[PDB]
Length: 330
Image 1: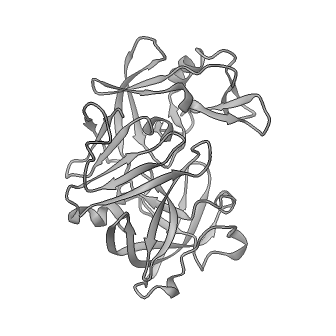
Image 2 (image 1 turned 45 degrees about the vertical axis):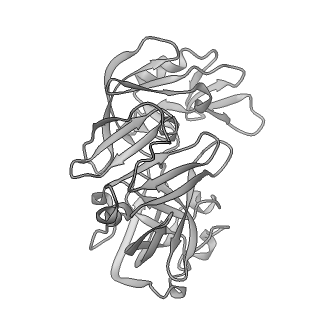
């Protein structure tokens, strides 16, 4: 089997991407944030505290003939931005782009933090990291990909995120029309439950490539590119008027400035992030100060190749017995 679904930016800045997902019988379609940095599929639901729902589409398991309570199961998650959610668990039929999993754990939110409430466009998350990070207790649950894997033509999914435009998540096949050149594959460590790999270096604009190992994770659920302070300082030093602002919480720059590209290494191959991808707009409405799309990972404890990086590539998440990551230009 295979599946193919379009993923769409939630706003004009590509702050996140949503993908429609069919849950239950008859189908209830919710727009979920596909997140290769976590491993829970959770949704706004008929059980979510009413004051914490504001515009989201909810899953109502009582209206699904295939929903079954996963008795005694609870879940609780917090994300790197300090947001959180928790609740109980149903199993149900879940389809993505024509690919169906029966008995998928669907984690129903009883509580969500304010940032979730305040974002009407995201109805929940669909985790695509390794199932060892799944928070369901007492019995940890599998991701949608893990459950689908054996049925797939090939044990892979691909992320093809758009810049200010829709893109595609495919399951079970590699669309050879969707990228240029070849796909370069690189080793993955699953020891922390992430798609963790090592970039071979970087360049800023037309500058010379610096060979240096940069461990990090491929995370579709993180918006920006978070890299070591040394790397990030070298980038923003090439932007007239850029500065790191403690009050704003990162590097900012005047949007009269031209942003250089940023290149990262994948083995001997190179992925180029165009300068425009690194502009996340005014820090507040009407401001001439713009927020940068490349920021320091110092304090996070890990480097994160988020959407800013990933949307410059066609990315293969290879879930073979020994997982690997592939990157192609597009």
